[PDB]
Image: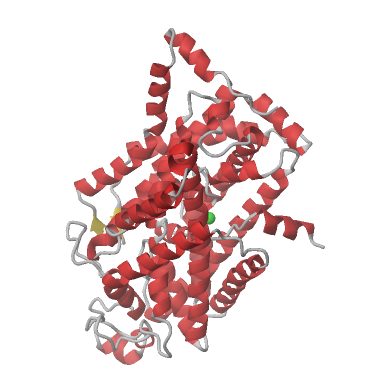
Amino acid sequence: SSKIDFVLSVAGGFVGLGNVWRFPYLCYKNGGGAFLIPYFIFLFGSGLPVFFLEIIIGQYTSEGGITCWEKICPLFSGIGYASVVIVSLLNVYYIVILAWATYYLFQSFQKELPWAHCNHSWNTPHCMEDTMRKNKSVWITISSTNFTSPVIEFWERNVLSLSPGIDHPGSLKWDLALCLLLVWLVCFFCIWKGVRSTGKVVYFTATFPFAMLLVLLVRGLTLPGAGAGIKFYLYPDITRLEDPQVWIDAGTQIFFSYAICLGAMTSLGSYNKYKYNSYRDCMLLGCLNSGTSFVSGFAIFSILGFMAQEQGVDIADVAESGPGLAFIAYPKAVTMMPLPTFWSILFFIMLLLLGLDSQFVEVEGQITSLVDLYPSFLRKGYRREIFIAFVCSISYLLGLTMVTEGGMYVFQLFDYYAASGVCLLWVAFFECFVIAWIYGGDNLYDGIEDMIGYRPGPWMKYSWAVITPVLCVGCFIFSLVKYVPLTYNKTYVYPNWAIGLGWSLALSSMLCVPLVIVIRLCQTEGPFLVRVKYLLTPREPNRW
Ligand SMILES: [Cl-]
């Protein structure tokens, strides 16, 4: 009987789209090895206390995401609303990945994969086979007039139908629309019916993704040219560390992967009992998720190095330097494996399930929070399923601007600004500030000692008071001083209106805390200092 494996299985899944898709693309965008020096360090902080913090706030107060902060500090109660806005913006574009994966799945039910060869309608005349790119006849006699890889051209001109800019929306893609509608219908059915068939299927849903990742890693390591990719992934560049965008991406990757600032962990902590040693389980889950991300990065960069040594170009210019790196990398190694159809279907089902689990968790948490906001209004009678369907339809309609011709730019904007970036750093800094300098570190340490049984070391308090807030403030100041506009595939410059829309989407969640502060100050009766003292005092009992 393995205690650690059993407790990590019963606790909850820790694999999703934030480690095989977010981490590899963020690492490839930020120079590769140079992305690992800050991230890992940041990881520790951004992994160990903060996540555990959300586990304790939900365990101590025994509340959800919105009502937990109403006991620690009624003044800074806008963190719950900020997390709700963040998850509402995340459910829009995070499920779009499940539409691209679904479309790839329906295109992998044939013997010959379409992205393998250039003999197709969507391919341009500049399409060339990867094996012919280094052939002496084509590489020497024929000039390299912007000849692109077949997989990249297939992806762009058949899945995204990329436009010259975001100003050009184009025509709506019926295939992506139908795939997204089917995924949303599956999500609505699983939510309204309730997912209770996980009594024994958890073993499969946990072993199959890890088995596929292991197979892909073994295949990538046994491919020629993987050494260059491994070196590019491991050997850092000190020049990239000066860029503030690298630190921002490194900080937001962990907050995205560990579901931090989403309020889901605060709800999961309420499910845990009071006298429960959550510290060990949190550390184990964090270390396992970090190891899974580190292993997936090895496979991604080995595939990238193989593609580089086959085509004959630099490692930083092999594929798209943005969202969609896995779809270029992994299908190539799948085609390189015998029987590409079976392995492709397996990988697509794995990715679809990993995305659907996180989507179910996030949407159920959001719906539960919105229902707890107005219980008698959104719970009595049949209005609960009506509200669920309304939220699903609104999210699907808001996700129709990312499946168009000019929809990839909106997807990049939502990935960079809406559910990640400045918003998550702001929320984490405010949470750490309220925990350390407002609520106190010693009282929380005594509470954790009473709950789990032993008082932790000085790492958590120092990270809540010093490490995480100062790091977040420094990253924000560095992004403000040396500000570079967002770029797509390092070749497209976003217009001023797109940057303004992204900053507005970010501020929509960022301003949830200051506005709630003003609302609470105006609602409370009395002098300003008396109101501040009343709203900073832990009025509601924290379940001592
Ligand atoms: Cl990660």
Q: What percent of the width, then of the height, locates residue 446?
A: 72, 28
Residue 9 shows in this picture: yes
Horizontal side of residue 270 vs 248, given as left or right: right
The relative height of residue 135 versus residue 287 in the rendered view (above or below) is: below
- At 53% from the left edge and 80% from the top edge, which residue is drawn? 223
Q: What percent of the width, then of the height, locates residue 46?
A: 55, 43
The relative height of residue 171 versus residue 153 in the rendered view (above or below) is: above
Residue 470 shows in this picture: no
Which residue sits furthest top?
527
Q: What percent of the width, then of the height, locates residue 47?
A: 59, 46
Work out which quarter of the rendered image holds the N terminus and state it. Answer: bottom right
Label count reads 0
Between 515 and 383, the one nearer to me in the picture: 383
- At 52% from the left edge and 15% from the top edge, which residue is drawn? 534
- At 27% from the left edge and 71% from the top edge, which residue is drawn? 174
* Colour scheme employed for the rendering of this structure: secondary structure
Horizontal side of residue 138 vs 376, given as left or right: left
- At 47% from the left edge and 62% from the top edge, which residue is drawn? 189
Horizontal side of residue 19 vs 109, given as left or right: right
Q: In which quarter of the view is residue 85 placed?
A: top left
The relative height of residue 223 versus residue 407 in the rendered view (above or below) is: below
Work out which quarter of the rendered image holds the C terminus and state it. Answer: top right
Which residue sits furthest right?
1
Q: What percent of the width, then of the height, locates residue 44?
A: 60, 45
Q: In which quarter of the view is residue 29 placed?
A: bottom left
